Amino acid sequence: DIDEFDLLEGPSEKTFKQRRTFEQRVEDVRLIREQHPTKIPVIIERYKGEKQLPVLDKTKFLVPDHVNMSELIKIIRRRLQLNANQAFFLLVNGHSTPISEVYESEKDEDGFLYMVYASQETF
Amino acid sequence: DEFDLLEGPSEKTFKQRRTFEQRVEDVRLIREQHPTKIPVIIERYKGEKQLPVLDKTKFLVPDHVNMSELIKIIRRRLQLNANQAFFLLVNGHSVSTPISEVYESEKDEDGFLYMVYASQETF
Amino acid sequence: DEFDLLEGPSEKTFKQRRTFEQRVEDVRLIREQHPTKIPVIIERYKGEKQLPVLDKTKFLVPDHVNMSELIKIIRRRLQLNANQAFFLLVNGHSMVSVSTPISEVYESEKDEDGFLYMVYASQETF
Amino acid sequence: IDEFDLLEGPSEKTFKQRRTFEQRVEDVRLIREQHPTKIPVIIERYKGEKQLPVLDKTKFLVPDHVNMSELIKIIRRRLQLNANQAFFLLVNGHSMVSVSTPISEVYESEKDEDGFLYMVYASQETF
Image 1: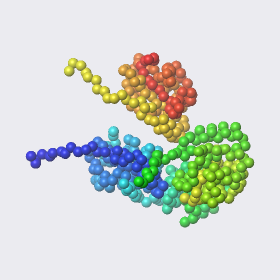
Image 2: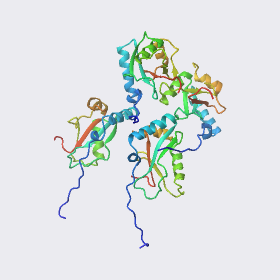
Image 3: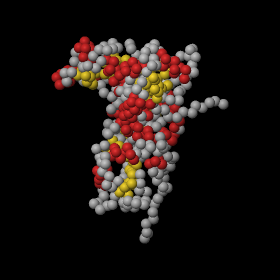
Image 4: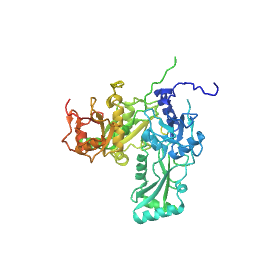
């Protein structure tokens, strides 16, 4: 009996936007941008169908505008404590340079830049 | 609820991303090929907290452009609003003179003209 | 019991609501039709907490208006008395002092798109 | 077991139904500031179309050097059609078949108030 596991069916993983109202997200960005004008408000979440990489401990981040995607990837890799073999991809609008430029092009209606990470470059 | 601020690697200067010999060679070709254009480095001041980062660092400025015209060009590349202060410092110095005269007085050992911009005049 | 502030997404600036080519064609039409008037964008500072907003953003300033007269015009649209602080900023510089023809300001300060951009606020530095 | 049973969800919403007349204008404003030589076009399959396949995307950029005849030919091989297949591209109720005028002229006369040029494709020319 205790040779076998019982998987507990849990609730669905919920995204940041369903965890926080759009007005709270706009007030979040508005306050953080007036007071930290050189830092980009970034949402980083695990791809919903991801089954190799662990979950990050936080979701809402502020990234200095001089940080590029390659440096950001390395930061998230140590936060997840990945080993050198583990694959990691960070997707903005499904697509795998300084973040401020990504921010100006891809930021959300609510002012956040949304990113999704996975162990594959795929959809 | 609160943001988690990610700090990245140090903002490293142009002289830190390119060796003195590569920079010397950069100038030598561009001045041999564009004798009437000034090779200019424009970087955001190190402790700058309000202005955004520029997308490029290495610029060519026609030799007849004056400092006042260059400031307006940079203000518009940064998409600044009319209220936003902007100062362009050459060797710490913040005008109706042609860039070619500034180039002859202030150019670096490597042949580049170095400029730093900030929202404050002096530091 | 407490007030709750209703905010939407950031309202966009004039340059964010109209392309560079639409603005150039805006200016070319208005300069062909009003040869003695200067096209000026006047917007309230994004973080302004004291001065009211104007209904309009796109303005024509007759060439006989100097900077001192223009300041008084905008102050009186805002219904300020002589007491209240008011600053009108062009390319990062507040223009209280100038009291100069609008055509000179336009020719020295206009944007590449042909508009002269101004921001007003109750503070001079940010 | 002899016959197939059709799987269907609620009616799919068109682009104009999935996007308010603010998200669409604001889309055009960024894309036209950023790609001044490309025309923003919505291309959707006729809602009752039973012959032509669906495209993966709805929002397209057409370079200004593309004329209507070349655009049709682009969509036809994007759909991987045979040489037969009837294919008609309709704008504001009109079949674009023998137009061949530059896309920017089509755009300026036929664009929507929101700034998109709307097109629908089908294997029939009338409805």
